[PDB]
Image: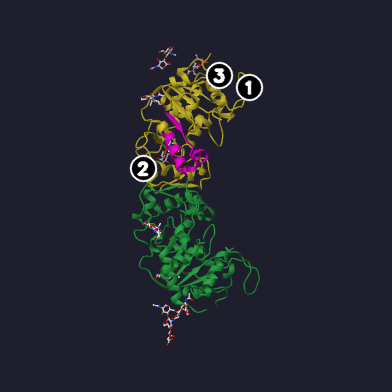
Chain colours: A green, B yellow
Amino acid sequence: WKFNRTAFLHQRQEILQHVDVIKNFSLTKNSVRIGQLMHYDYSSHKYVFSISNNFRSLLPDVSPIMNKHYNICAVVGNSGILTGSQCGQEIDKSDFVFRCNFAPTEAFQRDVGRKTNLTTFNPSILEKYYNNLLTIQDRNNFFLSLKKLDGAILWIPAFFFHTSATVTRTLVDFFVEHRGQLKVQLAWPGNIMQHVNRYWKNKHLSPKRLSTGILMYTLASAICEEIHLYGFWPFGFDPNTREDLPYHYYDLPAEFQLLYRMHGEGLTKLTLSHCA
Amino acid sequence: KWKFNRTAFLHQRQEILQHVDVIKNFSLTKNSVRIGQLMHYDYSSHKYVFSISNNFRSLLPDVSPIMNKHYNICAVVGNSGILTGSQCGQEIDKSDFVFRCNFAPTEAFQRDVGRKTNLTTFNPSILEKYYNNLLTIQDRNNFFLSLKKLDGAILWIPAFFFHTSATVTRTLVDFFVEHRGQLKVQLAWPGNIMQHVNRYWKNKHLSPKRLSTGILMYTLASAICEEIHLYGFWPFGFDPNTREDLPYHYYDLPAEFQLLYRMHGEGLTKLTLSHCA
Ligand SMILES: *[C@@H]1O[C@H](CO)[C@@H](O[C@@H]2O[C@H](CO)[C@@H](O[C@@H]3O[C@H](CO[C@H]4O[C@H](CO)[C@@H](O)[C@H](O)[C@@H]4O)[C@@H](O)[C@H](O)[C@@H]3O)[C@H](O)[C@H]2NC(C)=O)[C@H](O)[C@H]1NC(C)=O
Ligand SMILES: *[C@@H]1O[C@H](CO[C@@H]2O[C@@H](C)[C@@H](O)[C@@H](O)[C@@H]2O)[C@@H](O[C@@H]2O[C@H](CO)[C@@H](O[C@@H]3O[C@H](CO)[C@@H](O)[C@H](O)[C@@H]3O)[C@H](O)[C@H]2NC(C)=O)[C@H](O)[C@H]1NC(C)=O
Ligand SMILES: *[C@@H]1O[C@H](CO)[C@@H](O[C@@H]2O[C@H](CO)[C@@H](O)[C@H](O)[C@H]2NC(C)=O)[C@H](O)[C@H]1NC(C)=O
Ligand SMILES: *[C@@H]1O[C@H](CO)[C@@H](O[C@@H]2O[C@H](CO)[C@@H](O)[C@H](O)[C@H]2NC(C)=O)[C@H](O)[C@H]1NC(C)=O
Ligand SMILES: *[C@@H]1O[C@H](CO)[C@@H](O[C@@H]2O[C@H](CO)[C@@H](O)[C@H](O)[C@H]2NC(C)=O)[C@H](O)[C@H]1NC(C)=O
Ligand SMILES: *[C@@H]1O[C@H](CO)[C@@H](O[C@@H]2O[C@H](CO)[C@@H](O)[C@H](O)[C@H]2NC(C)=O)[C@H](O)[C@H]1NC(C)=O
Ligand SMILES: *[C@@H]1O[C@H](CO)[C@@H](O[C@@H]2O[C@H](CO)[C@@H](O)[C@H](O)[C@H]2NC(C)=O)[C@H](O)[C@H]1NC(C)=O
Ligand SMILES: *[C@@H]1O[C@H](CO)[C@@H](O)[C@H](O)[C@H]1NC(C)=O
């Protein structure tokens, strides 16, 4: 695989033509009004969410990625293809590492690495893994997870699904209460998937719901000189051994075809094999 | 026929108020909680908590809404189907002060239940069941319109009875902060009070792991009413005079009712189980 820097910078210019990535990355204090009604990107337009004093107080003053430039970025998905890959060292060598859905690293360091600079957080994760922060034990566990992220950006898409509404109110309340006690940088994208989906429409990727991986590649494109993908592999067998794989390392086929095409054209390095 | 025994009632009142500080228990107040304080739920495992936000606290009253209030005749109106066809409306509205349970509707049922409302209770689960969690403009407007019709009534919201109220409390709180100043409704939010209430009534032979909103209502009423009349308390699905079937609720626990019937017997209160004059 050889990196084609000119093709990549060209892809970047095309992306930024269709998506104002720095702006789209997160709402800012002055980009919303108290009382404003947000709609949900992937839900009926009739669903709304009112912006409280408190939600707004949790937004950044300027985009967390304004004037940031990193040389090598790793974007790490959650496929089982990472299990036994020993990609840990190669991933941690990167200048900036994106991860998906609050994925765990402590017990998987050798394969996925421990360095984290941005991680995505669907608010449904409170419900599934932290019991809606209903007990002291859960509130402490959540606090502790967030402390381990140090100064990483936590990218919370609250306005994708209307089913994230009630949990958004629990998160917001938790973050206000613990204001000043965490170095984690919150980022809250608004209604951005129409604009993101337009760029990728012209590259014949269609689907109902664009994946977090393609979305990550899109952000990464604005701030990384060179993107390497790890853990993107939708199928439940290994591509070299053909032995079975766990669906996720810690236990869509249209998207992956596209990334493999891009790997072919030297835009990015998709890694599907053991590292060391 | 029923005769009011005023001396027996005033005796019951003095006994209640000796064991329950009703005026205090009625609602938390701004200065009675701290931002960050963890509330527990009276009828749930002690492990469940709710943190008091800036916003929750801003919605509490500065003093108890029933401090130094005294009414002559109080009606306490439950929701049993026994009210259907009863024409109790006029007798209920004649009262000086009317308590109602669980945001019960009156517009379509005036002749039987009355229209006058001075306090109504509100389990926050009602947002999920009838207002779709305030998720749409239509639901937010419907809720706003219901609250506007209560004018200056107290809305008594027991947020800390069941842990399953937690998420919907956060939706209410947010709704009320957003609409601050636009409603004359007087919010009241009782804290952890059922230990103290249930202990007075333990010695009167009523046990349960959940006390009923009606007994709770009688307890509050006792602190501010000279004479209490109960309407719509009747747990069974048949009429006591005709024996024909009844809807469970007029708008569609047996231990508690036994107790209220005993009290009716002793002239403390008038339980009404029949058509009104
Ligand atoms: C609802 O009304 C209640 C009165 O019916 C309020 O209860 C009072 O609340 C205060 C503040 O929490 C308590 O003050 C404490 O007093 C005890 C004294 O020991 C007592 O132990 C039990 C009480 O259950 C009993 O044996 C005697 O009352 C004893 O005197 C101290 O340990 C504390 O430091 C503190 O000063 C009152 O004791 C308490 N009264 C009763 C009868 O329990 C209650 O706070 C109200 N709740 C709300 C939300 O308004
Ligand atoms: C940004 O990163 C690029 C590319 O870095 C390369 O690939 C990464 C994924 C990692 O594996 C890196 O370890 C690896 O360097 C950097 O460009 C590279 O710079 C180095 C010099 O530091 C170049 O190597 C030299 O080449 C000359 C002539 O061929 C030799 O005489 C030298 O001894 C030495 O080997 C290399 O050509 C160049 N690589 C590419 C693909 O262009 C870049 O330095 C870095 N920038 C910053 C500011 O960090
Ligand atoms: C995401 O960026 C898009 C694209 O730049 C923004 O869409 C523009 O919004 C402006 C308002 O400032 C419109 O007048 C432009 O016509 C839009 N341009 C395009 C190409 O659609 C959008 O505001 C951004 N969304 C967020 C949440 O930041
Ligand atoms: C990207 O994230 C990692 C956190 O995982 C940052 O690396 C840490 O930097 C601190 C502060 O100097 C060190 O004390 C830690 O030992 C580093 N941890 C690891 C795991 O390497 C890194 O600095 C961040 N980089 C950028 C550009 O934000
Ligand atoms: C009203 O109720 C009171 C209290 O229950 C009655 O007064 C008691 O009457 C009994 C006789 O059955 C006496 O032995 C008690 O000493 C009285 N109690 C007190 C505290 O004085 C009263 O009789 C009732 N009135 C009516 C009309 O039934
Ligand atoms: C409290 O209300 C009662 C009930 O209406 C009042 O006493 C009654 O007064 C009416 C008419 O004024 C009479 O027809 C009843 O026969 C009375 N009943 C009894 C048992 O005395 C009482 O005066 C009211 N007190 C107030 C307004 O202070
Ligand atoms: C109890 O509630 C009713 C409202 O349900 C109050 O009665 C209203 O009072 C206003 C202003 O005094 C009148 O203009 C309305 O016509 C009355 N409505 C009804 C239905 O009677 C009553 O004042 C309240 N009682 C209190 C606070 O003691
Ligand atoms: C990528 O670089 C090659 C040289 O490797 C160049 O000729 C080509 O035009 C670039 N872009 C595309 C789209 O192939």
Q: Is residue B101 left or right of residue B235?
A: left
Percent coordinates x, y for residue A273 in the rendering: 57, 75
Between the C-alphas of marks 2 and 1, the distance is 50 Å
- Between discs 2 and 3, the one toward the N terminus: 2
* Numbered label attached to residue B244: 1
Residue at the extreme top: B1
Between the C-alphas of marks 1 and 3, the distance is 13 Å
Q: Give ligand 3's quarter of the image.
A: bottom left
Q: How would you rate the neighbour count of disc 1 (Cα within 10 Å): few for under 14, some for 14-19, many for 20 or more?
A: few
Between the C-alphas of marks 2 and 3, the distance is 44 Å
Q: Secondary structure at mark 1?
A: loop
Q: Are marks 1 and 3 in contact (CB under 8 Å)?
A: no
- Between discs 1 and 3, the one toward the N terminus: 1
Q: Which one is in front, B204 or B51?
A: B51
Q: Which one is in front, B259 or B272?
A: B272
Q: Amino acid at mark 2?
A: Ser
Q: Nearer the viewer, mark 1 or mark 3?
A: 1
Q: Is residue B95 left or right of residue A204?
A: left
Q: Same subunit under labels 1 and 3?
A: yes
Q: Is mark 1 within 8 Å of ligand 7?
A: no
Q: Amino acid at mark 3?
A: Ser
Q: Is mark 2 within 8 Å of ligand 1?
A: no
Label 1 resides on the chain identified as B
State the residue at coordinates (60%, 25%): B246
Q: Are marks 2 and 1 in contact (CB under 8 Å)?
A: no
Q: Which residues are magenta?
A: B118-147
Q: Are marks 2 and 3 in contact (CB under 8 Å)?
A: no
What residue does disc 2 label? B58
* Numbered label attached to residue B274: 3
Percent coordinates x, y for residue B204 in the rendering: 53, 28
